[PDB]
Image (cartoon, coloured by chain):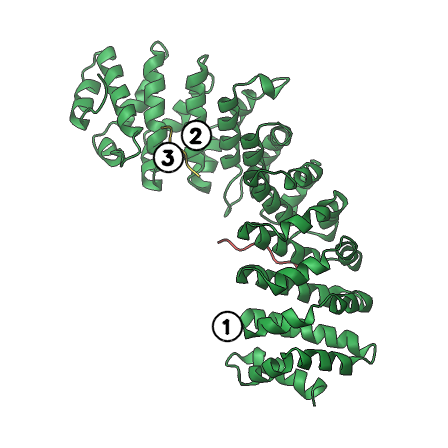
Chain colours: A green, B yellow, C red
Amino acid sequence: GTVNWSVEDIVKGINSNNLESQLQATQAARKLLSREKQPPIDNIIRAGLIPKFVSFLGKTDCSPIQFESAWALTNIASGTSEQTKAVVDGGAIPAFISLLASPHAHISEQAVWALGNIAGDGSAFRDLVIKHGAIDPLLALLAVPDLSTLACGYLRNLTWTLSNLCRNKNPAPPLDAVEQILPTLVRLLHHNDPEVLADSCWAISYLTDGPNERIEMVVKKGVVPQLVKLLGATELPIVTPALRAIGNIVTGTDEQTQKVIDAGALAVFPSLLTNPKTNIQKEATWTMSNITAGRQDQIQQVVNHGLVPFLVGVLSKADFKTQKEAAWAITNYTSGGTVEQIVYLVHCGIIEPLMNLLSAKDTKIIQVILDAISNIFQAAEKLGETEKLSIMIEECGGLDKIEALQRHENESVYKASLNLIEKYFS
Amino acid sequence: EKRPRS
Amino acid sequence: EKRPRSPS
């Protein structure tokens, strides 16, 4: 009898001051807010029902109305920022944190869910949820000897909410909150549920998306080997955040990059650099570009793992945004690599796909490619072999393209393209 | 990410 | 050098 009420009828029941009439109107509101087709969230808000729902959260003597109002508020909070703000403005944050201690599992789970929606709105509400003290009772729900004893959906909701507490930048989450959460994240990262694993990886990817000090907090917990293992998962929803975290880590110091290499990550990149999902190839190639921007011994590990032919492959054929990352990987490679490493790069056939990408109507990748050509010529000068490279570039049509770039509009494109020809093709 | 309960 | 990830 609570199906398809009007908002007016819901208001009538909630204003009735009959607890059972209030409970049924609240359930009717929950069912209204649970429909896929355009749930009347704004009409419920404008009816002034949020403070009433929040008040119902505190009725410990009537657990069903706590549950129904928590569910109704969860779905309002899952909407726009203005709709989430209406829930927060109703005082729902401390009420939901109090419900985390509920003896009813389905009620505390709803409070977990609601706080995840609120924290997921942005850094402001995230930090406000933290200031209200949500982390201690949330982590206390996971303080069991074995996570497998917890209900699966319950554990998935807790992991997701914890990930939203790790989410967003400007500012990043408070340092002490991250330290408080991380040991539980590491444990969730070893759980055997695919959705817990995915959301745990997402949380780690958020925490590593920052300066080296943030990356270091994660790396010192020793999770890089587990991240590398999850890099090899068959589930794309796990590989994607695991790869984002690995890529974030290698934006840090050479020592942090080395932890990724030491853990065996490069052995997965033959598959990642040919992955059918465009986003995986792009992320994997971007990651490779930050590894080839490392030390010469790290460039050498890329060589030993047979990854240069795979970089030649993505440069030859990939989505353009992936080919752009491949161009960066080559320019970084030639900028920091030894003469012998650069020679090997030419031997793998980098020149022709490099030249072909000078056709691209992207002024930055042209600058990137021209830089790599200069770097390769500089290594050819140290060998006295610039003539042979000049022949290679012309034979594949590269010099025709470089000379067309002399009439290019953007400045450093045509300055650099004349310097190449003036010096090596003249 | 926000999630409604359907 | 290293290139951190774009916000997009």
* Category of crowding for the residue at label 3, using alpha-carbon neighbours closer than 10 angstroms: few (below 14), some (14–19), many (at least 20): many
Which amino acid type corresponds to the residue marked 2 in the rendered image?
Answer: Leu
Q: Report if residue A159 is visible in the image.
A: yes
What chain letter is assigned to the residue under label 3?
A
Question: Which residue is nearer to you in this view: A169 or A43?
Answer: A43
* Category of crowding for the residue at label 2, using alpha-carbon neighbours closer than 10 angstroms: few (below 14), some (14–19), many (at least 20): many
Which amino acid type corresponds to the residue marked 1 in the rendered image?
Answer: Lys
Q: Separation of disc 3 and disc 2 at Cα?
A: 10 Å
Residue, disc 2: A115
| Residue A113 higher or lower than A343, as above or below | above
For marks 2 and 1, the one nearer the N-term is 2
- Report the mark closest to the observer, 3 or 2: 3
Which amino acid type corresponds to the residue marked 3 in the rendered image?
Answer: Ser
Residue, disc 1: A361
Q: Report if residue A293 is visible in the image.
A: no
**Which quadrant, please, contains the C terminus of chain B?**
top left
Q: Separation of disc 2 and disc 1 at Cα?
A: 46 Å
Point 59% across, 19% down: residue = A148
What chain letter is assigned to the residue under label 1?
A
| Residue A9 higher or lower than A219, as above or below | above
Q: Position of residue A113 (x, y in %)?
A: 43, 28
Residue, disc 3: A78
Q: Quadrant of residue A72?
A: top left
Task: Give the secondary structure at mark 3.
Answer: loop
